[PDB]
Length: 339
RNA sequence: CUUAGAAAAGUACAGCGCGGCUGAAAUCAUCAUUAAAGCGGUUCACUGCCGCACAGGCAG
Image 1 (cartoon, chains in turn green, yellow):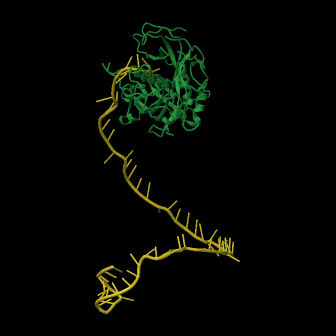
Image 2 (image 1 turned 135 degrees about the vertical axis):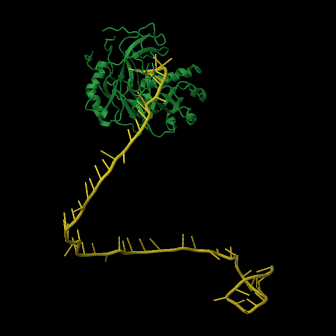
Image 3 (image 1 turned 180 degrees about the vertical axis):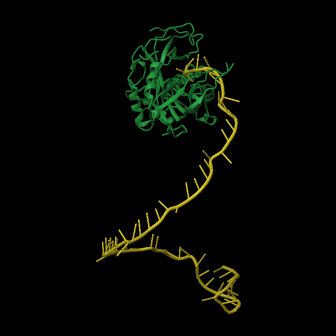
């Protein structure tokens, strides 16, 4: 059982339980980990260490979303569990308008969960994106201990989210059914690394992770020759073979209330909202059964707003490169243009 | 180092019957395109013969 509320305050352009009155329940923390099936992940809390945390959905926000989202069919998505919880649909559709820069163009993931946050559906969570990037870092570190990626940028080419279902394995018969959205986003990403020299492509593609947000991210064989390292992103951007796509940025304007959220959504119905970071409800503490013996802390997902940026002249890369700032009260990946 | 680790929604199907858009019309008077202009072989493919040839063949 968890009852503790938010410990700390968040910036105005990030959403958490602190911005809304949480007295919609149905302060002690005492949970089990060894036999429980709750989720558990690891993120870097420092340049040389990681932090384990188990993001748990806050029923306050889910209710605050179910109550408001009715009569908003244009931006409402419904799901039945085992019970009907409506969430925030992402617009209507997806249109298609240092040195040593490394590219992995045209990465397609098939069957990636779109229920990033418990109160929205759409593009997969940027937390999962950063986890995939860091898994790539770990895989490439075994063959080269001096390889670090300072920051990355994500370009989306094709986005498609529709209702599907997971056929649970038999445990006799199959357990209670579950309905969750899935996505097949086609995306390309840029990497800023400190290697500062060329690396052989065979090990680079051998170390490329496949899993991405419970999906299968694989790159076409004929695009292997396009995996090359360039010293300048200005010429790197002119190089990838896809002339269509969008760049992801953060919405710095205020989104304090869900009414203001829907007001912001209705001017363009093109921006998307998904999980961007985690707000810890408990300070990092060690428990006997962690993911890898690191400090564990029950956290809560934060919903942000992803902007659309068309790269061109007079477009600073500082507005499109994301990284994990590792704040003491929350762990989130945001673009480095915000001070 | 990804609400991490895993997952087959699939089997059948006849939309069918019938139909009058019809009545009437004036597009309509007038009009100045005007002025001004080098496209240039220096030699180069000539002169004889035959044949009746506005025919067709010879040589230097």
